[PDB]
Amino acid sequence: INNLVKQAQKMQRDMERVQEELKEKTVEASAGGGAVTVVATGRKDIKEITIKPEVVDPDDVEMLQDLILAAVNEALRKADEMVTAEISKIT
Amino acid sequence: NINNLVKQAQKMQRDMERVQEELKEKTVEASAGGGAVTVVATGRKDIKEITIKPEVVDPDDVEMLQDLILAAVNEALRKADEMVTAEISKIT
């Protein structure tokens, strides 16, 4: 029972630390062969969005809509994945 | 005493199952640039739709668009978190 207590306590310390660490850790996704790039943190805050002017065309807003949507969703997916990895490492 | 605990725990169980299911399809919406960029996200923080008005689409000013998309997405994601909290409060 002693070693279980210490193990659970360690898991609790590790979890509080990884929570902090994940706030600033980031992932990156892009779409359109690098025309759109999205950086998200481990808390799923979008930190940055970079768009190349070649896909910015007021007569083809659907292109940019599609591209933003794909890169944002893939960035959010990667952030979920990073969180799971970090939790797996400490459990 | 025991019967009521069984009843309350079963209710909690089905309500939580139901709410999880409904949040997958329920959406929230957020806007920036005076309605120029509108983002729809689900209760699972999937982005469902982004609508961009051509008035903010200028290849000589990609920063305008970056800025409005970042704001709109971040606010949509925050509204998604708030809806999940709200739906859980209703079952607790």
Image (spheres, coloured by chain):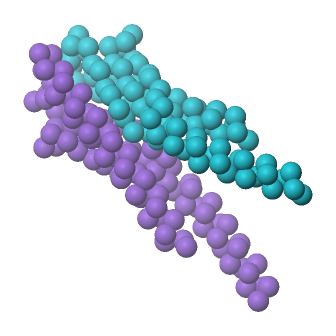
Chain colours: A cyan, B purple
Residue B81 location (% of width, % of height):
43, 53
Q: Is residue B25 visible?
A: no
In the picture, measured across the screen, residue B56 lies left or right of residue A80, that is left
Figure check: A58 above or below A13: above
Residue A70 location (% of width, % of height):
41, 26
Residue at the spot x=62%, y=35% of the render? A86
Residue at the spot x=58%, y=32% of the render? A81
Q: Quadrant of the N terminus of chain B?
A: bottom right
For the image shown, how many numbered marks are present on the structure?
A: 0
Residue with the most extreme bottom position: B1
Q: Quadrant of residue B50?
A: top left
Residue A71 location (% of width, % of height):
40, 25
Q: Quadrant of the C terminus of chain B?
A: bottom right
Figure check: A90 above or below B12: above
Q: Is residue A1 visible?
A: yes
Residue at the spot x=13%, y=20% of the render? B61
Residue at the spot x=58%, y=37% of the render? A83
Residue A56 location (% of width, % of height):
20, 18
Figure check: A29 above or below A6: above
Q: Quadrant of residue A73?
A: top left
| Camera-side residue of B79 and A2 | A2
Q: Quadrant of residue B18?
A: bottom right
Figure check: A58 above or below A85: above
Residue with the most extreme right position: A1
In the picture, measured across the screen, residue B65 lies left or right of residue A79, that is left
